[PDB]
Image (spheres, one colour):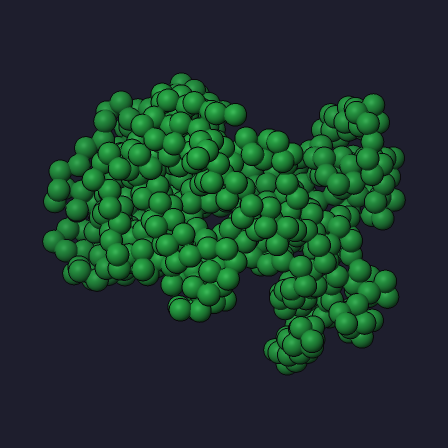
Length: 284
Length: 284
Length: 10
């Protein structure tokens, strides 16, 4: 009984297939700390995964997709090395963990031809227009905030560690009031609200590179300049507000950005299409 | 009265092209609020841009290359809108700053043609064998530190505001050594040499979300996990160091990774190959 | 410059 987890077009997903990876997950998850969904939905996920792998792996079988031997060969030896292992000695580590050479070899090629016909197909799907590139590049210029030295002030409206939305909405709205009346000094308003060590000192954090800022701030100061007031940004400790005080590689950064931004969209899209336009029967 | 800035294959950059682009540059620098180098090396920058612009552009013609009349106009609309103006409003800005709209429109089509050619030509060069899309994919597996929880300790080594080679070297030296002893307690080395406040509490620094950390740590953290030592990293205050304490669509990340690094790598490669395959004399 | 002053909020 090759118990069948499900049917994808003119082929199947087994319980073997599922009950297998379904483990390698909980392993390579508790082997790197990150906890997991419900064993119920986790399955449902591993299902969706395995189904898709089929559609597109069939799509593979349909089109003339082989993967050369030298190629697969190289491919393994390079993750052998990567996780701190070796050639023949690889064999006797998963062969010593439940598997064979061919539970991996044939199993990796499946990964490889899947990667192939999945890119190869969303590749033919993306088209960047000069307009898009030009337009974007002109904007990534307005942002030109690289190692952009930057003085700024700070207002903290702090929340407790784990508040309800009743404790949050007060700070949330209270900020936007200060946000507006800041634009109509901040330094005075900082002492009158801010709850950090540099609060009574007027929110004054001082000069400092945009890099040295907490990542989440650098995401919103990127598009701003002298006088600007960004926020209110919510983090671990509550809502922050900031007042700003001072300050042919764009035709590439633009393109790399689109050629990427687009591929990520026009792949999510390409499966939405393959999934919904195929035979997906699931046997409980 | 209009000289030749430079011959560049049988065709020229003009002193006018340059002294007009130096106008387009310091026009931004005052508004963008960033200083420029010596007007002497700066001319030698713009010169070098305009030279390159040319080598490419001559390729523009060499192989026929248009720009959709509609695209050109569109980008310009899109660049107008991106700056909070209509064409009608922008028009006046072109007049007030002093440029013929059609000098400008044609000036853009210049930019657009160049891009067309650089990109079209770099994309040509990029070759991604699967043997490497796999390997890399199975390297970002044990890495995906997205909105991760993360507890750290932290040494800091002291460095004055404007440091001296000796200090800086003898500092990084001590900072390396601490790290060399760090992979052999860390908290007890806080107390030893950490310049910072937390040192007594052990550099003990608590749970941070990777994104809430300073962006100049993030770079070297996503590729590391519990029990690891990071840095020494250079910053304003000086040299940091830190312990860690707690914590397909990766073939998407994987491909994008390459599709991207390979472009950036192979543009920079082709550029230098074109300034090579080229007569070019500058006439100051 | 402030890298720290600031980190010491998170």
